[PDB]
Length: 330
Ligand SMILES: O=C(CNCCc1c[nH]c2ccccc12)Nc1scc(-c2ccccc2)c1C(=O)NCc1ccccc1
Image (cartoon, rainbow, N blue to C red):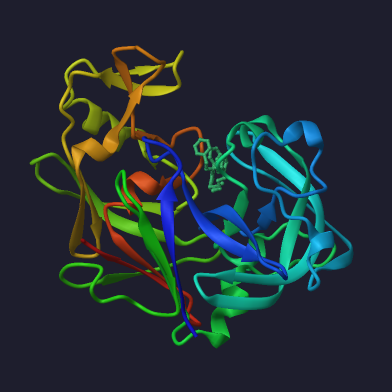
């Protein structure tokens, strides 16, 4: 089997992408944020504290003839911004772009933090990191991809995120029309639960390429590119008037600037992120100070190849017995 679904930016900045997901019988369609940096499929629901729902579409398990309460199971997650959600668990039929998994754990939120409440366009998350990170207790659950894998024509999914435009998530096949040249594959470590790999270096603009190993994760659920302070300083040094602002929370630059591209290595191959991808707009409405899309990972503890990086590529998440990652230009 295979599936194919369009993923759509939630706003003009590409702050996140949402993909429609069918849950239950009759289908309930929710717009989920596909997240290769976590492993829980959690949704706004009929159980969510009413004051914490502000425009989201909710999953109502009582209206699904295939929903079953996973007795005694609970879940609780928090992320690096200090956002969180928690609740109980149903199993139900979940379909993505024509690919159906029966018996998928659907984590129904009883509580969500303010950041999620305020994002009316995101109805939940669909995790695609390794199932070792799933938070359900006392019986850990498998991700959608893990449940689908053995049914897929090939044990892969691909992320083809657009820049200010829709893109695609495919399951079970590689669309050879969606990229240019070749896919370069690189090794993955699953030890932290993530699609963790090592970039071979970087370049700023038309600058010479620096060969250096940069370990990080391929994370569709993180907006920006978080890299070591040395690398990030070298980038912003090529932007007149750019500075790191502790009051704003990172590197800012004059909105009148033209940003240089950023290149990262994949083996002997190179992926170029155009400068426009690195512009995240005014720090506040009407400001002439713009927020940068490349930021330091120094307080995080891991480097994160988020959407700013991934949207410059066609990315293969290869879930074979030894997983790997593939990158192609497009
Ligand atoms: O959690 C994910 C992917 N799920 C995102 C869900 C989500 C969290 N608010 C959301 C809001 C909307 C949609 C999805 C999400 N990736 C990872 S691995 C390590 C960190 C981390 C650890 C410590 C410190 C910082 C990052 C994160 C992280 O928190 N990224 C987002 C971020 C990146 C930079 C700064 C803050 C948060």
